[PDB]
Image (tube, rainbow, N blue to C red; front, side):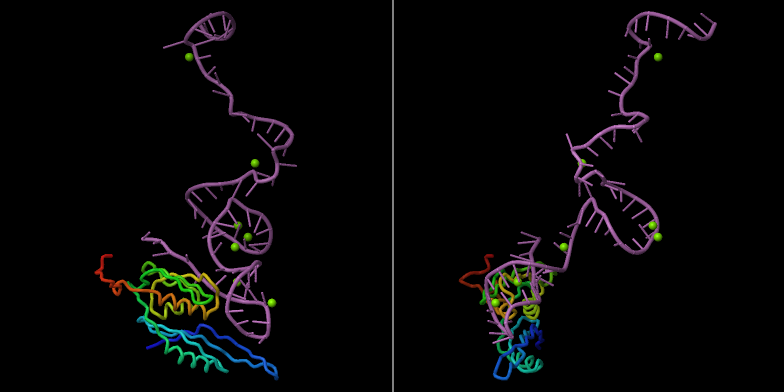
Length: 152
RNA sequence: AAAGAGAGUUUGAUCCUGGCUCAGGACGAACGCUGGCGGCGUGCCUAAUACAUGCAAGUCGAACGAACGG
Ligand SMILES: [Mg+2]
Ligand SMILES: [Mg+2]
Ligand SMILES: [Mg+2]
Ligand SMILES: [Mg+2]
Ligand SMILES: [Mg+2]
Ligand SMILES: [Mg+2]
Ligand SMILES: [Mg+2]
């Protein structure tokens, strides 16, 4: 069905009259290997509770990934916020080369061979969001009709 | 056909800009602890500072003027 890949655990704090209070936040990316992937985010007082909340949150925001010939159809770069990820196709059997969160999302999507690079900041949530944006900017060869056959 | 990996550190916690440090490759290398063999290579980067000593450029009698042999 769906797997789970925990990307980050952070101990976050807020200060009140009686000192300060801490609570953990989790970023979790889930998906199946057939081409559906999505990320979530939780915030709870104990780590497993945050993991469960993030898992339940991610299973509402999925997206399809076009994977001609088990790789990305073309090159495209995502620019959400302070994040910057570009994705390029790769030769067969080359594996996945990416940072932490980018690797997580690209493998959980099921894409086998792809090479990327992070050209902006290194905030994990912004890296995930930029990768998802870059994925959304993709387009397949067959669905581009625009009154045309293949002629490619 | 070829095609790019990041991480730690400013804050009570954030997101940005920003430097510093680490993870790879290579030596005509040197130092430290160890050290079996074979093949193929390499070895004064500094004082173009000073040289003890051996060798590193000679050869033609079929171009021409002496002695040993007889
Ligand atoms: Mg930095
Ligand atoms: Mg400051
Ligand atoms: Mg080095
Ligand atoms: Mg020995
Ligand atoms: Mg010995
Ligand atoms: Mg010299
Ligand atoms: Mg003669």
